[PDB]
Length: 24
Length: 50
Ligand SMILES: *[C@@H]1O[C@H](CO)[C@@H](O)[C@H](O)[C@H]1NC(C)=O
Picture 1 (cartoon, chains in turn red, cyan):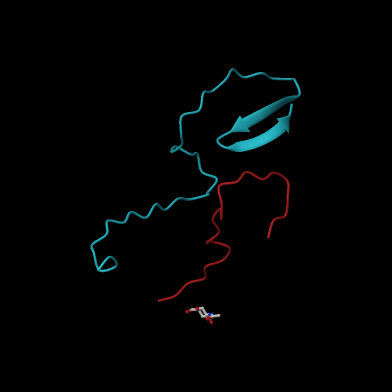
Picture 2 (cartoon, each protein chain N blue to C red; picture 1 turned 90 degrees about the vertical axis):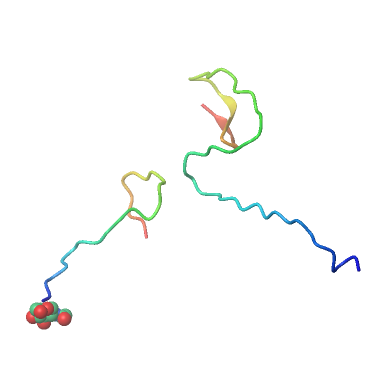
């Protein structure tokens, strides 16, 4: 069986704090 | 021969990650001064500011 993953599967790539920014 | 003799070797591997660090040499920690332009050192990070 299969199902839609949607927008799941996003983690923090590093432990550096960033605020109000669009980061690649 | 000298090269064929046994050698005890230790390789030290270390990480420059920005996690809270734990392993470093004996350095005295001074008092904290706020709201003043001072030089500062935090876990080997050097800077100058308020
Ligand atoms: C994902 O799975 C569903 C059900 O198995 C199927 O209808 C759909 O076509 C699949 N989509 C892709 C992109 O594989």
